[PDB]
Amino acid sequence: PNLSYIIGKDTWVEHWPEEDECQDEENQKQCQDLGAFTESMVVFGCPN
């Protein structure tokens, strides 16, 4: 159970701004897209 994940080129890491930080105009679009995706990719799966 000592598994530790490895960061690589295939792995893309993006910071998710918090609810307070989501009020920013630049971050608002990213927050909305992440929130929509969190439900879409979880319920509808993926086309492939």
Image: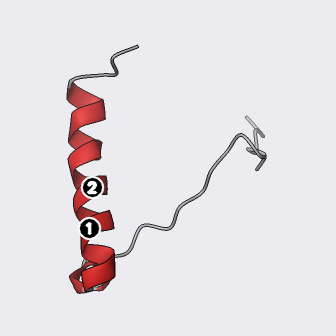
Residue drawn at x 28%, y 44% is 37
Colour convention:
secondary structure
* Side (left or right) of 14 relative to 1: left
Residue 32: image quadrant is: bottom left
Give the image location of residue 33, x and y in percent.
Answer: 27, 55
Q: Which residue is mark 2?
A: 33
Q: Is residue 16 left or right of residue 11?
A: left
> Which quadrant would residue 27 be assigned to in this image?
bottom left
**Alpha carbons under labels 1 and 2: distance apart:** 6 Å
Q: Position of residue 12 (x, y in %)?
A: 62, 50
**Residue in the picture at 41% in, 13% down:** 48
Q: Is residue 23 above or below residue 2?
A: below
Indicate the secondary structure of the residue bearing disc 2: helix
- Marks 1,2: beta carbons within 8 A: yes
| Other-residue count near label 2 (Cα within 10 Å), few / some / many at <14 / 14–19 / ≥20 | few
**Amino acid carrying mark 2 in the image:** Asp
Pinpoint residue 21: horizontal percent, then vertical percent.
31, 84
The residue that disc 1 covers is 29
Instruction: Give SS at disc 1.
Output: helix
Q: The N terminus lies in which quarter of the figure?
A: top right
Residue in the foreground of this view, choosing between 38 and 26: 26
Q: Nearer the viewer, residue 32 or 4?
A: 32
Q: Nearer the viewer, residue 45 or 4?
A: 45
Residue in the image at 50% along x and 67% along y: 15
- In the rendered image, residue 7, in percent from the top left (x then y), is placed at 76, 50
